[PDB]
Picture 1: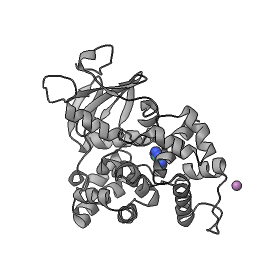
Picture 2: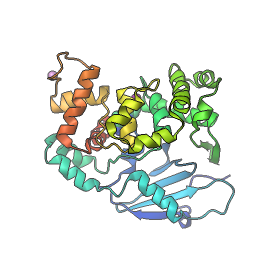
Picture 3: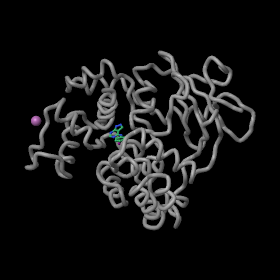
Picture 4: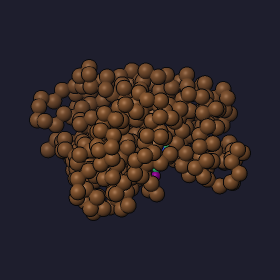
Length: 316
Ligand SMILES: Ic1ccc(Nc2ncnc3[nH]ncc23)cc1
Ligand code: NI
């Protein structure tokens, strides 16, 4: 019965946050391979789940409009102050992206050109667990197919929140749920393939070897290099996936994920080749070197600059 809200339909239930498009463009962020939990259900209206609640997000030129669906058959109302703070933290709007863009552009002419069109590409502050297992599913995959895997994984293992039109929303499952004896077999049935093993195995590892999700919070306050190494002990988690989690979940802005995409960008757009390393093609050593290159160039928010180029590279 209940359906997706729009700003025209039910404007009484919405609430705004002052946000220029220099700071945030929804359409360049919510589907740029950071989160896989957002979909443009109706034009310019992005629906998705955040911390066991569903949101719908739209924006004008200088406002970010948002509405919440609590789901527990309570009185529908506007977002509260605390829910708005949660969304503020999610987009990290405390950090000025306008000043970052100008800073990166001063030492990078290529970024300057791309920054013209692609403004408001910022990093989401994601839940560690959600980020971890999502990016375990990302190996040899694509954003469309990953989005399917994660959706199905949440329906099978996660708690139901609400239904809107013909879309049922589920919260992300806890580690215990993914660590069960039947979890791998079920995940293979859902089409994850070899990734099903890593999902189950990393669930068990975090519980048994690292002591639950408190560990991921410890890595959030630990240094980048400490957190990175710790993640790489998990099944299915290497340097690429570890860096993604660092950048997107563990508040390491200097983390620069190096996969085939950024290796292409580095070579084509910056003319970079591995100098310190001997081998011409990709390698663990050469990928690490390229990460160091971008940190040296861009500085302590190098991962944020990387996301601007990554997002721009998706759009042909
Ligand atoms: I397949 C697949 C899916 C998603 C990604 N996401 C990213 N990887 C590296 N840097 C990034 N910055 N923003 C997203 C992002 C990569 C490969
Ligand atoms: Ni070359």
